[PDB]
């Protein structure tokens, strides 16, 4: 199994265990303002496509989006 964060905050501690169908996590921006503590973290199947300024990250490791 894999572990991925599930909180908008950067230095948070909220996460969940990803099950089948999603062996990779992702972390992108949700807004330019207050971005310091605003990000879309969650599980996924593969690197989700999107803009470059969306700070879209992809990885398959324990809290890789830490």
Image: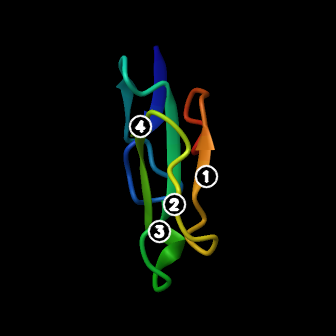
Label 2's element? strand
Which dot, 2 or 3, sits closer to the camera? Answer: 2
Distance from label 1 to label 4 (Cα)?
A: 11 Å
Identify which residue is drawn at 52% across, 32% down. Answer: 24
Would you identify the image quadrant in which residue 14 lies?
top left
Q: Position of residue 38 (x, y in %)?
A: 44, 68
Counting residues from the start of the chain, the first of labels 2 and 3 encountered is 2
Pointers 2 and 1 in contact (CB under 8 A)? yes
Nearer to me, 3 or 51 = 51
How far is mark 2 from mark 3, CA to CA? Answer: 12 Å
Q: Quadrant of residue 64?
A: top right
Instruction: Indicate whether 44 appears above or below 19.
Output: below
Q: Residue at x 37, y 17 (%)?
A: 20
* Left or right: where 30 falls relative to 62: left
Dots 3, 1 in contact, CB < 8 A:
no
Between disc 1 and disc 4, whose residue precedes? 4
Query: Height in image: 15 above or below 66?
Result: above
Secondary structure, mark 4, is: strand
Left or right of 66, for residue 16: left
Label 4 belongs to which residue? 43
Which label sits on residue 57?
1
Can you give x and y, in whole percent of width and height, for residue 55 in the image? 60, 65
Which residue is identified by label 2?
28
| Earlier residue among tags 3 and 1 | 3
Report which residue position mark 3 lands on: 37
Residue drawn at x 50%, y 75% is 35
């Amino acid at each position: 199994m894999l572990t991925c964060l599930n909180c908008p905050e950067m230095f948070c501690g909220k996460f969940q265990i990803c099950r089948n169908g999603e062996k990779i996590c992702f972390k992108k921006l949700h807004q330019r303002r207050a971005l310091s503590w605003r990000y879309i973290r969650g599980c996924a199947d593969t690197c989700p496509v999107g803009k470059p300024y969306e700070m879209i990250e992809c990885c398959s490791t324990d809290k890789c989006n830490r």
